[PDB]
Amino acid sequence: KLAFPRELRLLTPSQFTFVFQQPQRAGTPQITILGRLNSLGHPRIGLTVAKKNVRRAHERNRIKRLTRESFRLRQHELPAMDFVVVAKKGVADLDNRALSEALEKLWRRHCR
RNA sequence: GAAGCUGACCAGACAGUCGCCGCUUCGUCGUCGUCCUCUUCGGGGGAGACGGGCGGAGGGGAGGAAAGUCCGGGCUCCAUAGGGCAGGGUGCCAGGUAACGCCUGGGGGGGAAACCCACGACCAGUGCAACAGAGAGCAAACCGCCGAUGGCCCGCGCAAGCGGGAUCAGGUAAGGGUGAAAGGGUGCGGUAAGAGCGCACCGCGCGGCUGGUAACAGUCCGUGGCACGGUAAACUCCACCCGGAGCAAGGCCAAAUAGGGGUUCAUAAGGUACGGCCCGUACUGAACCCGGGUAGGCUGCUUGAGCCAGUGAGCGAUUGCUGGCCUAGAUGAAUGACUGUCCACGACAGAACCCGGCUUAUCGGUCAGUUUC
RNA sequence: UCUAUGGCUACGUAGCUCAGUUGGUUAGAGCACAUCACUCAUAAUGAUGGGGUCACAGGUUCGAAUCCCGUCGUAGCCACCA
Ligand SMILES: [Ca+2]
Ligand SMILES: [Ca+2]
Ligand SMILES: [Ca+2]
Ligand SMILES: [Ca+2]
Ligand SMILES: [Ca+2]
Ligand SMILES: [Ca+2]
Ligand SMILES: [Ca+2]
Ligand SMILES: [Ca+2]
Ligand SMILES: [Ca+2]
Ligand SMILES: [Ca+2]
Image 1 (cartoon, rainbow, N blue to C red):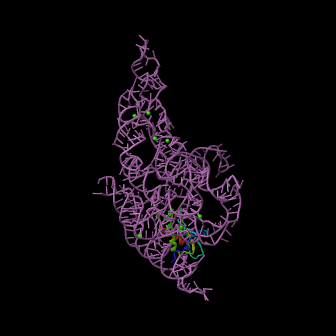
Image 2 (cartoon, rainbow, N blue to C red):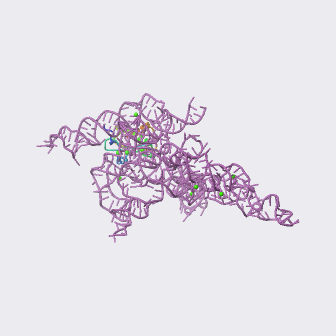
Image 3 (cartoon, protein in one colour):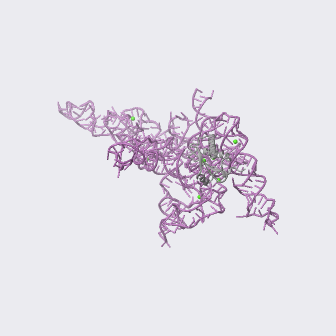
């Protein structure tokens, strides 16, 4: 069947800027999420892991894949909105379970 | 034959859901400027080149360094006839890939032979912080003193010159000596007793040789007596190599736009390129900056100067011949969770034009060798 | 507020801006604040603290901020048409 639908990701910088316009922000001192309303009917997610926040590329790939998996899992529940995630300094030392729970809590908060 | 140090490998693997990436293939939607065959187009057997157009089947996806440009190479457009520097690299020499700031045989050095080497030169230019130049360099009270022990009545020759002492001062004393690394010594009539100045030894310098394709060895004869001790990643010299730039090089397919200003121009050929300067080459306006968007599709992107097994060569790096093989290559950018096990309990770390290296991080183990009870 | 992977470019000395180049002295002014007659909570062309590992890891040298290779960090450029 169809693989991952590219219509659920932020590809061009235009969409990134559109989301960064005036989104609703929510996050912990580690990671934050900014969500805006769109007109496609399905939600979208974006990733933003800078090199200064995380130097090791393996950790960047790990966090990106974890966020994508969490989004794919909680896709039918989240509201039709485009989200963008941003990491900070102090997230590489977090474990998989703790980071997954934090992302789940952030998504539950963004649900409103 | 209880414990180190090199060396190749693994460092996470096996099975089950919810998910990413692509390749081949089965059934379909279509374009075809190939049309085989029906081809009067309100169609149809269509064979195939193709496409986020689709529903299934198979086998696969972190590397051991994908981490850093620190090197060389395949390709590419930018663009060049030849002579010279400047600034860059290779440097014990020899062999192999196309080669290298790659690997290996041999020699040499380094106090661990106890296992390393960024190891050419200086008998043309420069320096070498002594604070007494005695680490380019000439001698300082300080002991020495050979030259008459220049002389200086202290004794006498108060009558030819002699004894002593030191005159410590007016003489080079380069011989040990204290002053951060110091012109070779072990011993000698070693002058009136200081220095190869003279005598036996040399790892000190020049030429010859018997080993050896060379690097350099040498306990071998035959002399001249000394004419650098370093740093040469300190200037400089030699044997070879130097246009450089990167796949966000560029090569195609369409899709919305050389239209705009100042830098100066008979045949002086004044501007450009080979250069960063110079002889030379033949070709015509030149870069500072002002105008527009796309974020589209294909390649380089995964078939390598590789892999398996045998026959050879090379005392080794490496390479002649056979049978054969390849399931990631992307584009905000693929690896996750719950369970049964492993003990190798799972550290570092991630691919992106590519290949062969170089530097470093690299929890713990597998073995094949090397020092000590 | 943005942003990897790849090529090239410039550096890392008082908290901030700034120059020095084995010259052996082993190193320098201003901006944050106090002190001398501190003249209106600027004093002026003055001095007194300077609580700088000259970012980290090495090397020929007697010795290195300076010379050669290395690690980390920050900052900048890389899609074309007529
Ligand atoms: Ca396997
Ligand atoms: Ca590789
Ligand atoms: Ca010389
Ligand atoms: Ca000489
Ligand atoms: Ca002597
Ligand atoms: Ca002499
Ligand atoms: Ca271009
Ligand atoms: Ca591609
Ligand atoms: Ca990408
Ligand atoms: Ca990488």
